[PDB]
Image (tube, rainbow, N blue to C red; front, side, top):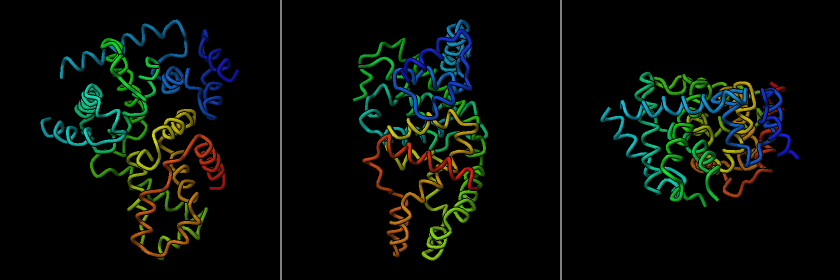
Length: 300
């Protein structure tokens, strides 16, 4: 019924992307998530009859990259990929190779950035969402090779689209990140001046914990199932990864205002902010976080 509404929008003939965005904000049912993400990111056209040709042509373009294609870029990627999360997925030997190849191709095609640790995490939600359209816990072993290459292309293009809205995060000296941490600081000074002063009082700088929140898009702070839900809304929002993300970070911080303000040791305060207790988090927790982020957007 919510699912029947998504399916009806997706069938077109010319899908209303405004209406799809407004529905996706509140989360996308799993059965339609892969095609919804593809449409909302602009990978596939709104016009239903154009989609198959466009998909096949974009996939072939990526396969041409693989054929056509630095030693130091590959060594950095070979060290990070093997030890990234979630370990059960990554340790599957076909997953590690796909991940390295996507990240290596992105890096040579974006020479102002190259490979920056943190971009490797942004591969995981696209890949897991897209591989889940072809499996019945995530084991890649049964997926035919042809289908797995198609997933890899889809993952590259959608990740590329995400990255094209946060370009300054990953250039030399990563000036997008510093700017976002500073705007986070200005935002929290205004919405929760008590949390702001306690951090100052105990010598915690926003950059010490929030660099990772911006660089990895909160993926090191919450479980993957949470990041997938969060990205439903990021893709529904205007400049979601870029601008709305800031407000999610502000809401994430002030969610533990009680535990922050009770913590008076600098070392444990920083440890806590870098290790927020979210292993048990579910969709209810993310929906609340987003509702708060949304409010903070209008307060500021």
